Image (spheres, rainbow, N blue to C red):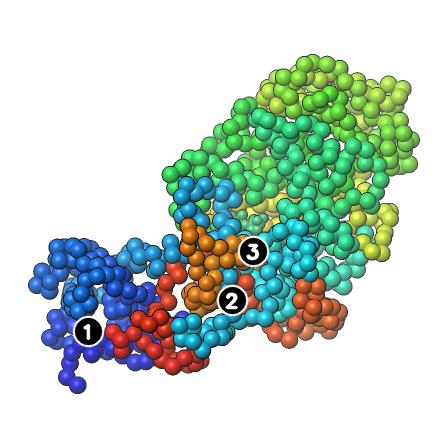
C-alpha cells in the first residue's frame, strides 16, 4: 500500500516490536510502529530504535483516552492548526463522539511527533507519559486499593500496612477474558500454617502469613529444601566462600518465625541436630544457640511440644517492662514484673521447667515504632506517610527530637527507667537476655562512635551479671510500688540453702526497683538468703537526685552494707525523678577480690534425650547482643564498616559478658529500600563484595569478623529471613486477589478485585541464587538422607531436593504486599479479552492485539 495511517500497526507481531510480560501487554509499555508522521501527509519508517508509548495509541477506556488528550494539550502539546487548543480539549470526556476522539488522538500524535523532532528524542515524551499515567487510578497505585485511602485513616507506627496485600492464585483458563498464568500455578501455597496451626486444625494463635514484600511459599517442598541449602551455606559461610575458614555462623535468629509455615522451624532444628548432635546434648545445643522472633505467646507451647529446637521470644516480658517502668503515666503495678512473663519469678528455685526463652528491653523494631510514632505526630495531614509519602527527612527530624527527649527527666517519647528495665532483665532467672546496640550507642552515628547516655549503667549491669548472677530467684514486693529481685548465687537453690559451690558465698545479687517517683523515704529489709549471713555487699548502683552513682557518691546508702546473722540486708530507699530513674534503682553485689565468673558449663547440667534447649543454669549463662539498628547509617569509609568496627572491638564484647552475637541480615539490600538494613534483599547468598559492600561491609570482612568474635570466645548468629524477599527487578504476569494479611479477600471502601492479571515484580535472586541455590543439596542428601525422607506436618511430604531454585519467581511465592504499580496496567480489548502476543514460549492464546496497532 502507499504511505498512510496503517503504519500505526506494530512493525512486527513479536517481542522485537512489542514489549510484553508473559505475552500480556501493559499500557505503560512501548512498541515500535511501522512508521510515524508529523503531519498526516509524509510517513517515515521507524528504525529499530524508534519506539513509542502505547498510551499514544491505546487506552483502557473512552474516559482515559479523553484524559490523555486533555492532559497532553495542557502540558506542552498544544497546536491550533491541528484542532488542539486548551479550549476544544476543555470539555471532552467519555461521552464525546467516538470519531472526534479518534481524530483528536490521531492529530495529537502528529503534534507529539513534532515535539519528538524538535527535542531530537523521546525523553520529554517518556516523562509526560509517566506523569499522565500517575493521574489515572487504574494505571497507578491507587487502584490497588490501599487501606491508607479509607476516610480518617490513622497510620500505623510499624511502618507497614498489614492488610495491603495480594495473593497469587492459580489460573489455567482458556477463557480470554480470564487469561492464563499457569507458569505461576502451585499445588501448595498452604497459608497460615503458623505456630500451632501448622497442621491446619488449631488457629488459636491467628498468626498471619503475610507481613510485607514478596511472601515466600514456605509450604512448597522445593522451597523447604532450598531453606536447608541456605542454612547449610550460612553455617559454613567462610569455608564455602574461600574466605576466613573460621568465618562460619553458629546459629540463627529466625526472622518472622510466627509468619512462615512452621515446617521450616522443624526442618532447621532437624538439620542442626543432624550436623551438630544438639538434641539431648546441652553442650552442643548451646554452642549452636538459635532463637525465634515472635510476638505470639502460643509459640511457647509449640516449642515445648517440639522439644524446644529454638528459644521462644518472651515478648510479654518486654511489654511488662514498658507498661510497669517505661510510661510517663498510668504505670502498671510493680508486681507485674513478677507474674506477667512466660516465667513466674516469685520463687523460681527449680531448673529445666521453664520455657527456654530469650527476652529484651529494646530491639530495632521497638525503636522504629517510636521513631515512626514521632514522624506521624510531626506530619499529621499525610495519611500515606508510612507508605509512598514517607521521607527520610522526617526520620532525621524525629531522631533529633528523640535524642533530646531521651536526655530529659520528663520524657515525652523515649522510655522511662531504661537502666531499671535492664537491671531486671539482666538478673532474671530462666532467660537468655538480649541487649540492644542502640541502648549502648547512639544508633544513627557511625558504628560505635558515640556512647548512649545509658552506656555506663547497662555495661555495669552486664559485667556484674557474668560475675554474680546465678542460683534461685525470689521477687517480692517491699511495698505497693517497690520490689526486690534477689539471685542467691551459684549453687544456691533458694533462700534456705547453704550453697553447694565454691562460688556460692561470693555470688548473688539484689536488685531494687520502684516505679513511683514520689515514694516516701523508708527503710527496707532484703533477704539475701541463709548462704549470705554476716556478709559485706557493695553498692554497685544507687540513685541520686540527678542520676545514678557507682561509688555511693550522693545516695541514701554507703559503699558497703553488711547483712545480719540471718542474711537480711537493710537499705534506705525513696522516690526520685531524673533522666535515669523515675522511681528507684538500687543494686547490691557481694564484695570480692578481684575476678569471678559464675558461668555454669553445659556439661554439668541435666541432659534430657527429648529436649534440645533446656532452661537451666548453663543456658542462663548466655547473653545475646543485637548488633544493629534500622537507622544505622551508611558507612563513610572501609574503617567505618560495621564488620571492621566489630572485629576491632571483639574483646570488648567478651569483657561485657556477651556470649552470642546476633548479626544483622547480611544479604545484598534492595537499594531503594527504606532502611538498607538487609530484610529487604535481592540476593540471599551475596553478603557483599569489596567493590559493592552491603551497609555492614563485604562478605570477606564478615568472615574475618566472625572469626575475630570466635577468637574472643563468642558464638555468632545470623538473622535468617525465610518470610519474604523485596526488590525483584523482573516483572511477571500473575493472577491476583485483594486480601488481608491472612490471604482472605477483603473490600476497601466497598471495592475489591479477584482473579486479575497483575504485573508484579517477582523474579530475580541475583547471581548468588544462580550459583549457590540448591548447590549443597546432593551433599546434604548424601550425608543426612533423613532430611529428604521426613514428611513435613503441614504438607504430608518430605522436602524435595531434586529441583534447584536458581531464580525466584511467582510459583514459589504466596503473594505480595501492594507494589504501587496499579491493577489496570494489563491491556484488555473492548470485549474484556486480554491482549496477548503469541511468540516464543508464550502460547496460551493466539495473538490478539488492539485494533489501533492492528
Ligand atoms: O514497588 C516494587 C516492589 O514492591 C514490593 O515492595 C515494596 C512494598 O510493597 C512496600 O510495602 C514497601 O516496603 C517497605 C515497608 O513498607 C517498610 O516498612 C520497610 O519494611 C521493613 C520494616 O519496616 C522493618 O521493620 C523490617 O521488617 C522486619 C522486622 O525487622 C522483623 O523483626 C519482622 O517484623 O519481620 C519484618 C520483615 O522481615 O524490614 C522491612 C523490610 O525492609 O521497608 C520496606 C522496603 O523499603 O516498599 C517495597 C519496595 O519498594 C515488592 O516486594 C518488591 O519486590 C518490588 O520490587
Ligand atoms: O524512546 C525510549 C527508548 O526506546 C527504545 O527502547 C526500547 C528498546 O529498544 C527495546 O529493546 C525494549 O526494551 O523496549 C524499549 C521501549 O522503551 C530505544 O532502544 C531506547 O534507546 C530509547 O531511549
Ligand atoms: O549509600 C551508598 C553506599 O554506602 C555504603 O558504601 C560506602 C562504602 O562502604 C565506603 O567504603 C565508601 O566507599 O563509601 C561508600 C558510600 O559513599 C554501603 O556499603 C553501600 O551499600 C551503599 O550503596
Ligand atoms: Ca509468610
* Closer to viewer: mark 3 or mark 1: 3
The answer to whether residue 541 is seen in the rendering is no
Q: In the picture shown, does residue 9 fall above or below 475?
A: below
Contact? badges 3 and 1 (CB < 8 Å): no
Q: CA distance from mark 2 to mark 3?
A: 14 Å
**Residue 186, position as x, y percentages in the image:** 56, 70
Marker disc for residue 36: 1
Q: Is residue 736 left or right of residue 138?
A: right
User: How would you rate the neighbour count of disc 2 (Cα within 10 Å): few for under 14, some for 14-19, many for 20 or more?
Assistant: many
Marker disc for residue 169: 2
* Closer to viewer: mark 1 or mark 2: 2
Marker disc for residue 811: none
**Residue 478, position as x, y percentages in the image:** 75, 22
Residue at the (30%, 80%) spot, across then down:
12
Q: Which circle's residue, 3 or 1, is located before the other in the chain?
A: 1
What is the quadrant of residue 267 in the picture? bottom right
Q: CA distance from mark 1 to mark 2?
A: 41 Å
Task: Decide which of 724, 141 is in the foreground and name it.
Answer: 141
Task: Decide which of 38, 50 is in the foreground and name it.
Answer: 38
Which corner quadrant holds the N terminus?
bottom left
Residue found at the very far bottom of the displayed protein: 1
Label 2, secondary structure: give it. Answer: loop
Label 1, secondary structure: give it. Answer: strand
Residue at the (44%, 35%) spot, across then down:
377
**Residue 117, position as x, y percentages in the image:** 17, 66
Q: Is residue 565 left or right of residue 664?
A: right
Q: Which circle's residue, 1 or 2, is located before the other in the chain?
A: 1
**Residue placed under numbered mark 3 in the picture:** 742
Amino acid at each position: 500500500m502507499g504511505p498512510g495511517t496503517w503504519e500505526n500497526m506494530a512493525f512486527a507481531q513479536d517481542s522485537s516490536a512489542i514489549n510484553n510480560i508473559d505475552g500480556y501487554l501493559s499500557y505503560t509499555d512501548w512498541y515500535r510502529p511501522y512508521g510515524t508522521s508529523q503531519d498526516g501527509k509524509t510517513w517515515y519508517k521507524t528504525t529499530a530504535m524508534d519506539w513509542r508509548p502505547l498510551l499514544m495509541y491505546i487506552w483502557p477506556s473512552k474516559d482515559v483516552q479523553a484524559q490523555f488528550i486533555k492532559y497532553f494539550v495542557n502540558n506542552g502539546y498544544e497546536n491550533a492548526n491541528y484542532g488542539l487548543t486548551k479550549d476544544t480539549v476543555a470539555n471532552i470526556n467519555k461521552d464525546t463522539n467516538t470519531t472526534v476522539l479518534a481524530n483528536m488522538a490521531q492529530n495529537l500524535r502528529y503534534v507529539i511527533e513534532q515535539s519528538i523532532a524538535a527535542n531530537k528524542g523521546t525523553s520529554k515524551l517518556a516523562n509526560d507519559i509517566n506523569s499522565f499515567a500517575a493521574t489515572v487510578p487504574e494505571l497507578s497505585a491507587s487502584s490497588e486499593l490501599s487501606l491508607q485511602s479509607m476516610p480518617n485513616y490513622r497510620p500505623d507506627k510499624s511502618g507497614t500496612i498489614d492488610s495491603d496485600q495480594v495473593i497469587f492464585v492459580n489460573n489455567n483458563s482458556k477463557d480470554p477474558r480470564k487469561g492464563n498464568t499457569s507458569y505461576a500455578d502451585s499445588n501448595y501455597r498452604l497459608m497460615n500454617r503458623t505456630i500451632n496451626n501448622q497442621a491446619g486444625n488449631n488457629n488459636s494463635d491467628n498468626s498471619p502469613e503475610l507481613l510485607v514484600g514478596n511472601d515466600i511459599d514456605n509450604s512448597n517442598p522445593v522451597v523447604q529444601a532450598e531453606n536447608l541449602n541456605w542454612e547449610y551455606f550460612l553455617l559454613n559461610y567462610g569455608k564455602l566462600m574461600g574466605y576466613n575458614p573460621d568465618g562460619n555462623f553458629d546459629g540463627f535468629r529466625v526472622n518472622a518465625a510466627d509468619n512462615i509455615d512452621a515446617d521450616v522451624l522443624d526442618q532447621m532444628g532437624q538439620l542442626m541436630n543432624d550436623m551438630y548432635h544438639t538434641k539431648g546434648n546441652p553442650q552442643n545445643a548451646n554452642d549452636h544457640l538459635s532463637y525465634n522472633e515472635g510476638y505470639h505467646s502460643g509459640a511457647a507451647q509449640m516449642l515445648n511440644e517440639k522439644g524446644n529446637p529454638q528459644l521462644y521470644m518472651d515478648s510479654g516480658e518486654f511489654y511488662t517492662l514498658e507498661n510497669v517502668l517505661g510510661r510517663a503515666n498510668n504505670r502498671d503495678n510493680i508486681g507485674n514484673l513478677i507474674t506477667n512473663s512466660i516465667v513466674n519469678r516469685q520463687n523460681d528455685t527449680t531448673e529445666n521447667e521453664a520455657t527456654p526463652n530469650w527476652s529484651f528491653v529494646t530491639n530495632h523494631d521497638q525503636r522504629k515504632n517510636l521513631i515512626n510514632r514521632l514522624i506521624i505526630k510531626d506530619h499529621s495531614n499525610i495519611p500515606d506517610i508510612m507508605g509512598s509519602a514517607y521521607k527520610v527527612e522526617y526520620a532525621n527530624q524525629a531522631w533529633q527530637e528523640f535524642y533530646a527527649d531521651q536526655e530529659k527527666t520528663n520524657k515525652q517519647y523515649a522510655q522511662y527507667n531504661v537502666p531499671a528495665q535492664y537491671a531486671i532483665l539482666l538478673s532474671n532467672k530462666d532467660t537468655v537476655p538480649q541487649v540492644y546496640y542502640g541502648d549502648l550507642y547512639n544508633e544513627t552515628a557511625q558504628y560505635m562512635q558515640e556512647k548512649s547516655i545509658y552506656y555506663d549503667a547497662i555495661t555495669t549491669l552486664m559485667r556484674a551479671r557474668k560475675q554474680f548472677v546465678s542460683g534461685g530467684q525470689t521477687m517480692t514486693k517491699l511495698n505497693n510500688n517497690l520490689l526486690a529481685s534477689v539471685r542467691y548465687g551459684k549453687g544456691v537453690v533458694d533462700a534456705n540453702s547453704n550453697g553447694t559451690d565454691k562460688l556460692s558465698r561470693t555470688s548473688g545479687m539484689a536488685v531494687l526497683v520502684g516505679n513511683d517517683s514520689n515514694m516516701a523515704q523508708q527503710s527496707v529489709a532484703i533477704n539475701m538468703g541463709r548462704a549470705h549471713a554476716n556478709q559485706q555487699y557493695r553498692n554497685l548502683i544507687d540513685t541520686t537526685e540527678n542520676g545514678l552513682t557507682y561509688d555511693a557518691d550522693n545516695s541514701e546508702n554507703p559503699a558497703i552494707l553488711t547483712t545480719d546473722s540471718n542474711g537480711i540486708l537493710k537499705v534506705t530507699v525513696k522516690g526520685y525523678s531524673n533522666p535515669y530513674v523515675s522511681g528507684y534503682l538500687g543494686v547490691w553485689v557481694p564484695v570480692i577480690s578481684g575476678d569471678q565468673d559464675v558461668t555454669t558449663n553445659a556439661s554439668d547440667v541435666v541432659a534430657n534425650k527429648e529436649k534440645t534447649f533446656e532452661s537451666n543454669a548453663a543456658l542462663d549463662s548466655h547473653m545475646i547482643y543485637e548488633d544493629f539498628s534500622l537507622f544505622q547509617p551508611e558507612p563513610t569509609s572501609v574503617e567505618n564498616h560495621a564488620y571492621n568496627v566489630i572485629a576491632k572491638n571483639a574483646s570488648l564484647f567478651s569483657d561485657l559478658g556477651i556470649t552470642d552475637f546476633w548479626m544483622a541480615p547480611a544479604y545484598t539490600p534492595f537499594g531503594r529500600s527504606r532502611y538498607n538494613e538487609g530484610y529487604s534483599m535481592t540476593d540471599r547468598y551475596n553478603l557483599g563484595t569489596t567493590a559493592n559492600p552491603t551497609k555492614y561491609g563485604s562478605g570477606e570482612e564478615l568472615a574475618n569478623t566472625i572469626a575475630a568474635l570466635h577468637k574472643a570466645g563468642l558464638k555468632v548468629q545470623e538473622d535468617i529471613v525465610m518470610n519474604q524477599m523485596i526488590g525483584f527487578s523482573g516483572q511477571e504476569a500473575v493472577t491476583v486477589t485483594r486480601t488481608n494479611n491472612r490471604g482472605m479477600q477483603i473490600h476497601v471502601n466497598g471495592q475489591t478485585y479477584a482473579n486479575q492479571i497483575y504485573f508484579a515484580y517477582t523474579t530475580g535472586g541475583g547471581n548468588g541464587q544462580e550459583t549457590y541455590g540448591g548447590k549443597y543439596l546432593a551433599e546434604l542428601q548424601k550425608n543426612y538422607p533423613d532430611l529428604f525422607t521426613t514428611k513435613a506436618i503441614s504438607t504430608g511430604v518430605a522436602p524435595d531436593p531434586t529441583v534447584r531454585i536458581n531464580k525466584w519467581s511467582a510459583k514459589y511465592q504466596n503473594g505480595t504486599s501492594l507494589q504501587n504499580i496499579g491493577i489496570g496496567l494489563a491491556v484488555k480489548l473492548a470485549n474484556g479479552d486480554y491482549a496477548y502476543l503469541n511468540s516464543g514460549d508464550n502460547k496460551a492464546f493466539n495473538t490478539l492485539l488492539p485494533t489501533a496497532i492492528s
